[PDB]
Image (cartoon, rainbow over all chains, first blue to last red; front, top):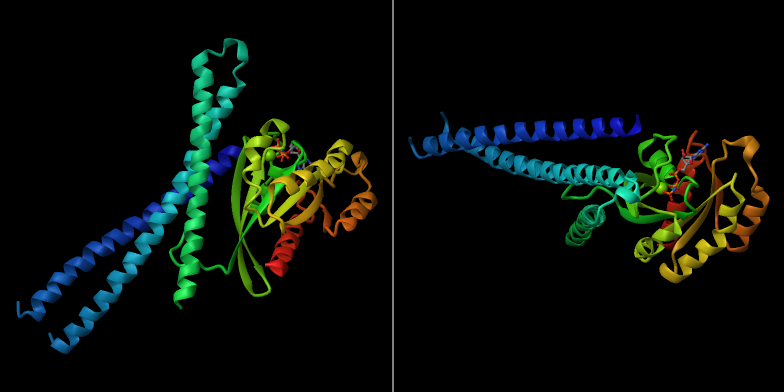
Amino acid sequence: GHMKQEELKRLYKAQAIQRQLEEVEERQRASEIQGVRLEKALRGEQDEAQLLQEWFKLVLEKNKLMRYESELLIMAQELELEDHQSRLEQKLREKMLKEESQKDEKDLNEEQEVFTELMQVIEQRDKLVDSLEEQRIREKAED
Amino acid sequence: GHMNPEYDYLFKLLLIGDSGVGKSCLLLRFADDTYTESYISTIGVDFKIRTIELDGKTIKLQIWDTAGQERFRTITSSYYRGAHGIIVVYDVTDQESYANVKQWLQEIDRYASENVNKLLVGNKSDLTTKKVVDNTTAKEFADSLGIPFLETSAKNATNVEQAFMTMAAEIKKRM
Ligand SMILES: Nc1nc2c(ncn2[C@@H]2O[C@H](COP(=O)(O)OP(=O)(O)NP(=O)(O)O)[C@@H](O)[C@H]2O)c(=O)[nH]1
Ligand SMILES: [Mg+2]
């Protein structure tokens, strides 16, 4: 049904974020290795103008990878909040289908608790939107 | 979820109106282009995000969905103040939901910002034989308030995109 599709789409997208992240960290591992190989070569252990051009591009590349990794970490965080929200909602819907007579005083307490966690997760998603917006306003003002 | 944001404006929208008129389905149709026949009542509040394009401007819409039952009024009223625009939804097959629109308008005066934009939506226009709210009376009410008015079907998507675009253009003109 509708709920399963939404879960499947969410899971695929978390999985794909994770894949990009895994590749980035690999490229960071390799670039660091190339980094020490370049230092050694410049320090005297090909052409040194050429080495320097290589060192320059490595520096740019480390920055590129850093900004990519940080973008992916934020996306992954956003997705985990949504996934968390969905499981809280379904946990709460299930407690609510339980008819009131058989509803122990500990059930009422858990409904209140699940509800509280649900509203807090929603509030975390909202403050993440507000944080992005703040950052937009600052970058605009700087430029 | 970037560090450098590629949009020009963030608008916060709110959907209000009676329970069962189709608020959650409108949001689902607009933000995700899907639709469920299931009647899964909303627990307090929720929101989705969709980005749109308006006169060369990229606009991020944060759209809040609220429970319509009176029982949730205290919980949902906290969310009115920060809205740039509020959409009041009724069901064209449901006379009492249209009747309540005056009440929803007073909730807006009580809890929302002074200059919030407003839009009136009659949902479920696909239900041809079951329609009971004449769009003449709805339109003439909306006009007396200077409010835009649209009829929609979340089910077959008619006018859904246009409803939110119209709301966003009204805010942009204001803001
Ligand atoms: N035929 C038709 N049915 C619709 C349409 N929009 C919603 N419905 C149906 O009407 C019911 C109510 O949907 P829903 O979006 O949950 O209403 P709501 O306004 O969010 N209710 P609540 O405030 O309790 O959360 C569902 O069965 C839904 O499928 C529409 O455009 N056409
Ligand atoms: Mg709803």
